[PDB]
Length: 277
Length: 275
Image 1: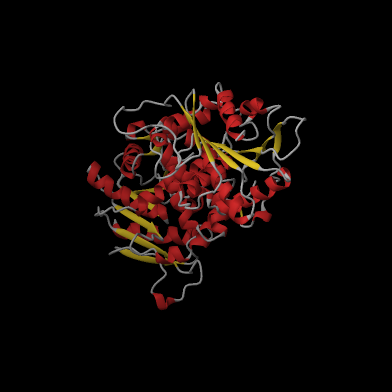
Image 2: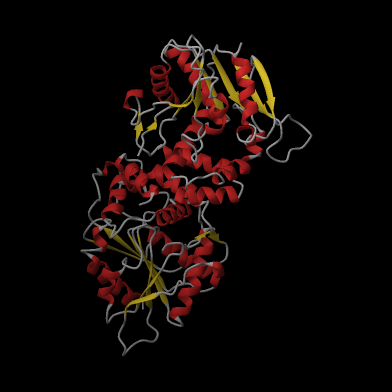
């Protein structure tokens, strides 16, 4: 396939994941982009992946999965987790613009507006709870705030699954290689060069200074097993968020928490939603 | 039709050739390489593109064309020019390593060594005169110095056709778009991503500090028409070299000098060699 994928595979083998992510971000600058939400390529129509109880569909929060940055991801991302929401809550997955041709966002705000427009449309008057994993968790928070500040519509809550925000993603750097190896282990097919570019541009967006903090209550869900050797003399390897409303620990690592242990993620969510309501 | 060429196509459209060359150099670091000239993956056998007079078979210097960095280039770079050397001089084109899964050179010196070894094998006991055009002209000079100091075989002369050496080469930066546009026109086929990366890597080698000067006399051949617009204000737009043996001006621009007007470049070389 593409040269970017082959270069990345080598960088990962050489333990230079971070360096190549910078190269992707620089190269993404030369892709055509959209400078206004209404100029976005794709239909950002959210897909219904689970349906809540018909007896009670009116006043209850609906869940919206915020697709993460992984170049190997897309519509498969919340398949496993969503199953556990069937007959409990509507679960809607919103695509991240610029993936599976597609113009890349000029800046993050522009992408977030396009998602906001599409989520408000599908959700209607139901309160929204945003959910994301890993970089998708950082995206879920930036979206929540944008919704509050730019659209005057704060979500009723945010579920952040293993967020590593700037100021404390040191374990994520030490686990760099395992992170890169995890991208390759997860491909159902070769990651396209265009999607690697989109990943690099978003990673760069997410490293930048974004001081807006959402007023929505946060559930912080954390992996219980380390992805790699750590050694706690350095401090905590675990995911972090400032002042969470509730924290739930679940089995598995940064990656396995979302597959084999997805039901435990779902159970903490459902239980947190009942309390909040 | 890989992504690097599509990005490069867009960069040239947006007048950002310089910036994108930097991205190619950066990305090139992640391609497999060779650290020793012996580890070079390809055969750098020079190809004979013109033959000298069957008559005289004495000393007689042999022209060695040092292929440039163009990702759309290769064995066809000197075809037009060499025609004018037929029945005058042997003309040999040496390939530039890393083009045509070819390992890229870890640094410039490693590439010049692999070239120096193949040139010596071909040139036998004859004197060698390097010739290069534009970035190939810079390469020709860096190779001459490498031949002289690391192979104990100093060339008998160097022809630098429209060179724009670092730190004092601005017009070629201002004519950026025209170069990128020139790469696309003239592609016999789509430039591969591996060759674009090779081009980026050499470009960066050639922007770097290289004090070593060759002892061989230089013929500086300069284009007569500007490639693009240029304010009569500050600056001669012309190619340049420090203290050349002879300077020769020929019709055409940076590009056409090697095409329609190649015979004029050839005339200048023959005359100069005759001394």
